Length: 134
Image (cartoon, rainbow, N blue to C red; front, side, top):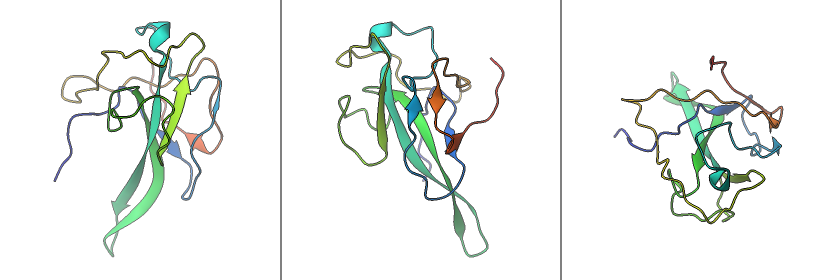
């Protein structure tokens, strides 16, 4: 079965190794995006276990975490701040975490992922992400 629909608007951040704790952010941890009202500058990072083909089956690869605006994505059911394993909540100064964007999710058939930029900091050194030009 192939899951389809709620892909993140942004590229993933990726743990450098196995058994890595959730990302911590310098600054807000909300990805750069000029096309969002400041009131709606809030969301969550969600962990996705990754795998790679193996001889014995498929082998673990370090986790990826994907960003979703609050009330969208695999954890659309959650309110900002709700406790859930594999969910880290983020919000910028000026954000009203009750507000809901219509950003929805990305259709990979129509739109490529946005490059990730954090002008106010970014995730800790446990994490990395691929270079994509703006």
